[PDB]
Image: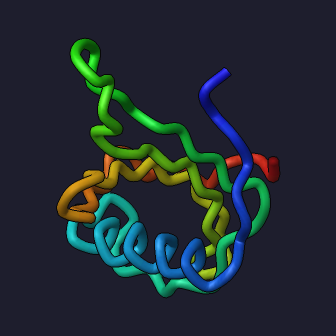
Amino acid sequence: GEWEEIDIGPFTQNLGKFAVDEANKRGQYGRLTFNKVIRPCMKKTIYENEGFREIKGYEYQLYVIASDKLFRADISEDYKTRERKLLRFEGPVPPP
């Protein structure tokens, strides 16, 4: 399986902040205030399909508490540029 649990240290918390910033732009929940990312944070690596199967990027699934509510965010991150995209941000979700 290509998903693996990663740490919820500062880089992951900053991913959650990105997710909340992007969720605020989408506005589905109105303005939210990032609180923290909780376990589990899952990452999967996306590879090119052919050639050297270079890593194309990553996808993360995060559980982020924002405005005291728990959301699940899916975030892509390009390997070469570090460009992140919020793919999904939903909740309030059950605690994982």
Q: How is the image coloured?
A: rainbow
Q: Is residue 43 left or right of residue 83?
A: right
Q: Residue at x 65, y 59 (%)?
A: 63
Pinpoint residue 47: horizontal percent, then vertical percent.
35, 28
Residue, x 29% and y 52% (percent of image)?
79
Looking at the picture, how far across and down is residue 52, in whole percent?
A: 28, 24
Q: Quadrant of the N terminus?
A: top right
- Asked if residue 30 is positioned above or below residue 54 in the image, the reply reads below
Outermost residue toward the front in this view: 52
Q: Is residue 33 left or right of residue 4?
A: left
Front residue of this view, candidates 52 and 19: 52
Q: Residue at left 49%, top 86%?
A: 33
- Quarter occupied by residue 10: bottom right
> Which quadrant of the view contains residue 30?
bottom left
Q: Up-down: is 13 above or below 43?
A: below
Q: Is residue 58 above or below residue 26?
A: above
Task: Please provide percent x and percent y for residue 50.
Answer: 24, 13
- Count of numbered marks: 0
Residue 45 location in percent, x, y? Answer: 47, 38
